[PDB]
Length: 319
Length: 319
Ligand SMILES: NC(=O)c1ccc[n+]([C@@H]2O[C@H](COP(=O)([O-])OP(=O)(O)OC[C@H]3O[C@@H](n4cnc5c(N)ncnc54)[C@H](O)[C@@H]3O)[C@@H](O)[C@H]2O)c1
Ligand SMILES: NC(=O)c1ccc[n+]([C@@H]2O[C@H](COP(=O)([O-])OP(=O)(O)OC[C@H]3O[C@@H](n4cnc5c(N)ncnc54)[C@H](O)[C@@H]3O)[C@@H](O)[C@H]2O)c1
Image 1 (cartoon, helix red, strand yellow):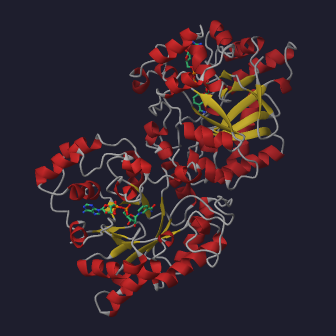
Image 2 (cartoon, protein in one colour):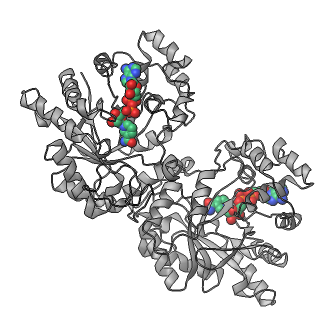
Image 3 (cartoon, helix red, strand yellow):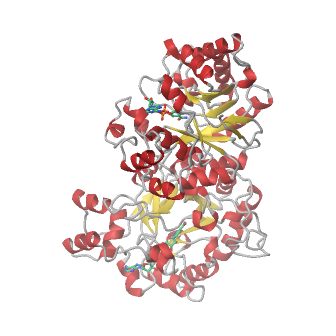
């Protein structure tokens, strides 16, 4: 029932997954276990989320009861900023494999085109914005291609099935494609009605790169973080346009926001933090949006971005 | 007098220059010569403008008459898109050096972060959007850093005093600073009240990279090319905000548009096609815009870009 997408790497990836950002460590396993019982097979995690160990417990439990087999679960992780230096990539990937308790990951992405100064794992993990000098941000000179090559070596070693990037703008993705042997299979970016970036999507998809959208509900995710920008932003759930369309097909505005991405061949990893939400977030492909619909949602685009490194320390990623 | 800007390379660069784009071949010579007589010392040229030979004649005459010395002329040139591949960088700089009739260029910039397929000088020069296969675009897999490394060499060889980039978005500039030994000394981008990219300026400058703005008169230059987007844009010279401010200080809209950039440490290279405009475009630093003035102009920024590779062949540089 949950459609698959063949990545450029030849491997399949579910178009509907379970998000692991802000998934409390205390119940992450229980919740990952439940997600699996509900049909979810892909889990979007990351080293920065600091719950790969619990996410692992969840997957292991499901396997031990015989509900699924390793190859049926698609695990996605992300290399954090402090580990871009070629000599530390495998080290971080090892930690991820150790916490997840697996021999490989299905998808490993460059979390950010930012390279923080290396902080030994034993000193602090996950490092977060810690750069080894108190509260100061510190960076290290490591071009993106150097990091990508280490990743390619790790793919030949069988430690990673598919590799990709996250939070990459169009010009950086183009330049990585000029020196990549294995081309990025995925581009994961903030995608929602307030930040559509239609040209980026068009380029990537035309380039054979698969798109995975995060924060499909826009500011909602950051409101729960008490962020000034997101709070000042009208929710998509109560927006006249989304509501109208939702009423025309007799659906929920939530189902509309996800269908809007799925219908265009984009993968989603909604954050289901309630049982009822687990089901809803993977049962939305029951209707079709018309050209008119897309044109209406298209008007909501104002280029509003919630996840911006510019807020951290003025990192020019999106400027 | 025209204040200078000390580049990160150590060489001084005039804060005001003479643009050479669309400067006709038959009169290019005489025009450059007149500008020198008028006080201009810097000239922004480029292989793609197809007139560096005449630009050279111009400067040669000035020198021969004892008007100026080579050391007093700041010549900027740009590496066109077909010459990114390292083995072709030197030959292209060579053709520029002979055309200009000098041993070195004060500044060489990667015109665009786009690598067209190579086309021999003899087959066609300048190639423009020509790639070697009719009207089709053909690209080479050459990462920016490779081209940049080629340039660094050329500097050590005394064939270039300073290097830099042009039309590079934030993420791209950041990655280059990661693999560069000689940091880009200058960033040249489209810059005016409709496309202010304030964060880009801030980031670049705080990094010692000097900003050189182009198309300071907004849609103006591209209107003189019958470009659809430019013809449907209210001119900056008629805009109420600029009018009000100009009247206040009794200056021309043109003078206000150039001071807006200059008072903020950004260099300008207006194209002057009239003896009077030639003089005005370099005598606008006789007043200062107030904090309120900057606030009112700030409201104009709608991010309207007139020079976009997206129009050429959907090249994702600004997405
Ligand atoms: N690579 C990156 O930079 C990055 C950044 C952010 C998130 N992500 C990933 O993408 C996932 C989703 O993004 P997100 O964290 O912003 O969450 P989201 O946008 O999917 O959901 C945000 C919130 O909306 C609510 N919600 C979910 N389903 C709902 C429904 N049916 N009805 C009403 N409310 C509902 C929940 O309270 C939830 O916290 C993450 O879990 C993470 O794996 C990646
Ligand atoms: N690196 C790049 O990608 C790039 C792209 C475009 C231009 N440039 C450079 O920057 C320069 C400036 O850009 P541009 O050529 O597009 O145009 P501009 O902004 O210098 O001026 C555009 C037009 O306005 C008019 N103008 C000039 N001075 C005026 C005045 N005082 N009052 C009223 N009208 C006036 C002229 O007709 C001129 O053609 C070029 O000469 C070129 O060297 C670089």
